[PDB]
Length: 330
Image (tube, rainbow, N blue to C red; front, side, top):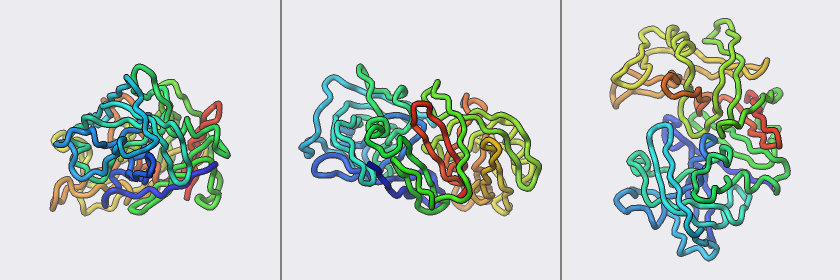
């Protein structure tokens, strides 16, 4: 089997991407944030505290003939940006882009943090990291990908995120029309539950390439590119007037700037992030100070190849017995 679904930016900045997901019988379609940095499929639901729902579409298990309470199971998750959610668990039929999993754990939110409530466009998350990170207790549950894997034509999914445009998540096949040149594959460590890999270095603009190992995670659920402070300083030093602002929470730059590109290494291959991808617009409405898309990972504890990086590539998440990651230009 295979699946193919379009993923669409939630706003003009590509702050995140939503993908329609069919849950239950008859289908209830919710728009989920596919997140290769976590491993819980959770949804706004009929059980979510009413004051914490503001415009989201909810899953109502009582209206699904295939929903079953997973008795005794609870979940609770905290994300890198400080947001959180928790609740109980149902199993139900879940389909993404024509690919159907029966008995998928659907984690029903009883509580969500303000960040989630305030984003009316995201109805929940669909985790695509390794199932060892799944938070369901006392019986850990598998991700949608892990459940689908054996049925897939090939044990892979791909992320093809758009810049200010829709893109695609495919399951079970590599669309050879969706990228240019060849795909370069690189080793993955699953020790921390993430799609963790080592970039071979970077360049700023038309500058020379610096060969240096940068360990980090491929994380579709993180907006920006978080890298070591040395690398980030070298980038922003090429933008007149750019500075790190403790009050804003990162590097800002004059909105009048033309940003240089940023290149990262994948083995001997190179992925180029155009400068425009690094612009996240005014820090507040009407400001001439703009927020940068490359930020320091210092104090996160991990480097994160978020959407800013990933949307510059066609990315293969290879879930073979020994997982790997592939990157191609597009």
